[PDB]
Length: 184
Ligand SMILES: [Zn+2]
Image (cartoon, rainbow, N blue to C red; front, top):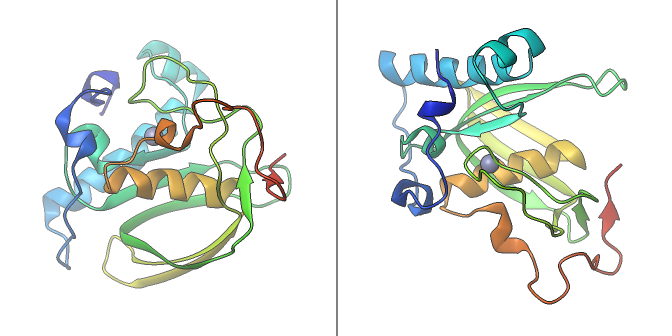
């Protein structure tokens, strides 16, 4: 199983590189890796398991975070009471279209690759449409909004060597952009 010791931290060169496109079909190893990435999220969200292995809870993970420069991500967002949940392992995910209007989490964002918290709003697109392949090479096209849209953009950013704090304004980190959607 993957644990915190597999998660590389801010400063590691791989986090700033541009992950390489995956050739389909994925190799056996690449599939096992993607499955392990999702499994890590599962474990991180289980109170008992996370405690036992000292895992930091999270809803997204990108291959670069475990030092694998490949364009693969895993997103595991639990039911928000709305009945909506997101359990996706994506290969070569790409935002094909998006809203002009932005959105942001009121408390900012966090990342397992960044040990300490960083204050500041991270404005992203409120709505996005992503096209990707799934673990078996089949086609997936997602229409996301709000929180999940923010999570996927955060993960895709990892594939381009972009960290969440790159989006935080230095002078006015907590000042919301006019007309931006505060995601509750
Ligand atoms: Zn992250």
